[PDB]
Image 1 (tube, helix red, strand yellow):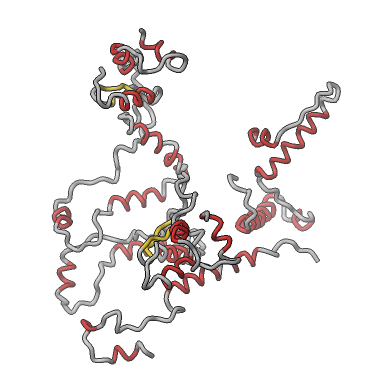
Image 2 (image 1 turned 45 degrees about the vertical axis):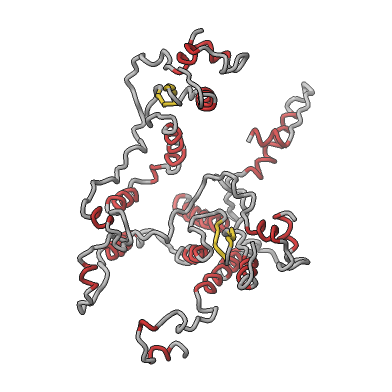
Length: 85
Length: 156
Length: 156
Length: 57
């Protein structure tokens, strides 16, 4: 959780090992007939500040859209995003 | 002229050099929270006592004193015993917080003459007289005053 | 003329023989990351301390010294104790990958005068003066320079 | 071959100095092997994990 900003293969070794275990976990709980019927299964990664810099950025575009009755434009510095994070 | 008011004026207007002798004496005495009864202490995990410690062997100390071309000084039984019993406590330790959140607080208190779980105001000899500091009010700007300016001359 | 720029020119144009005395002195001093505070270390599994070690027996050392036509030197109690406690759990939970990738890294650091978990820049005496190397910048082309060329003459 | 001759050589152990011992060739010191393991895993190890999951034709 604490560090995901690395794109090292050490995460990819861990990322494959936890995906294969959830396949076994879905095979035991979620009735293994579902496993071969469902197509490609993707485990989402825990988010990091490299993704979260854009995730916070789209919200202020949504903040403009719900203020369209009020016409209050909001724009956020790149320094201001990291202080929010 | 009152103990509490002068430290509110130290940031604003007046410095530390212009105080009275009876004002420097009063500002180093403890506050009114001292003498007020409060019988409660918590977090009895102190770094002062070592649970791995043992008696003087008096045969090893005889052997280590003769310089004996030896290869190990300490006894290493009780300090491997504490390593073994730590293996099974669990992940419940949440290590390096006691390493960081609790080690560095208790080290800085030992620099101020404060015991580890001691939540009250503690003395330390600065020059010729004592200064009662605590965790909460460190009185660091007084310690800068009574060390630097009080090298040659005397203040009470 | 600056510490950081010269090692970018060592691959390109100029060799090691044409540097100034004050430039060879500066390139062997540690970088600016030294003196910068960073209080964190990890992976406290060092091959420096042996958990199987024990005191000098002083009766066995008396017995082994007289050459005694004996058949075993060491004590073998604590080194069979560590073998037994390894089998009680190793078979529970371990894939190794550490005998390979943590032994050979710490051995190569001990040839550079670096402790095992030490992430910073470490000295080693080459000839007459010291060279501060680390894990990250091994400064191997300087060690080739100050051993080979500095056999007979002096550099600082 | 050079090391075998010294064990047959009728010298006392007191006369066996570092000089009488020939130096190992550089492959045989741990330095080399140690530096071999700087290389042989570390670079080669991530070559196994690259090209693993791109899948494309």
